[PDB]
Amino acid sequence: GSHMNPLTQAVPKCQRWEKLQNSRCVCKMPYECGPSLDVCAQDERSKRILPLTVCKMHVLHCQGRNYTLTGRDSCTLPASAEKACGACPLWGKCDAESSKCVCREASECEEEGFSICVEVNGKEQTMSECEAGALRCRGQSISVTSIRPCAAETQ
Image 1 (cartoon, rainbow, N blue to C red):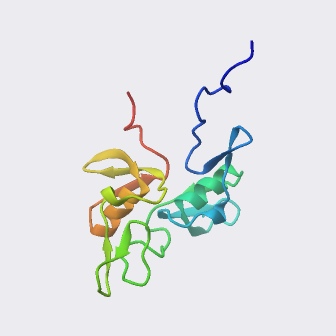
Image 2: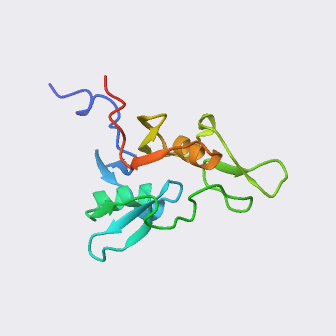
């Protein structure tokens, strides 16, 4: 007989830079992103270090664009550190009447948030963008190794 359920047997899970359409996982659009971690990447044709952001890089990467990642000192990011009220990311918001921006913790991760590999505590832990970002905002010492996940998650 026919399959009662399409060939996945559940709803297909697509990656952070992907969206499920036409029964497949396709990439989203890079301009459909904003809330993501700002990183320094090198353009393969220009060889310039340009500020990219995790979703931008990921989506554009799966769209067939080639970019090499560089160090956090290679470029200057819009948000490389803490922000102030009037301009806050997804891991940071303006608090109850102030001029500052407070950095939230991982427990307030509401927006999508990618999964990245960051070396914290001397270990490479895959955490969510909202978490790693919160850390980078609050003052936790974090060393982003890559915008891809770590092999921390392996059972």
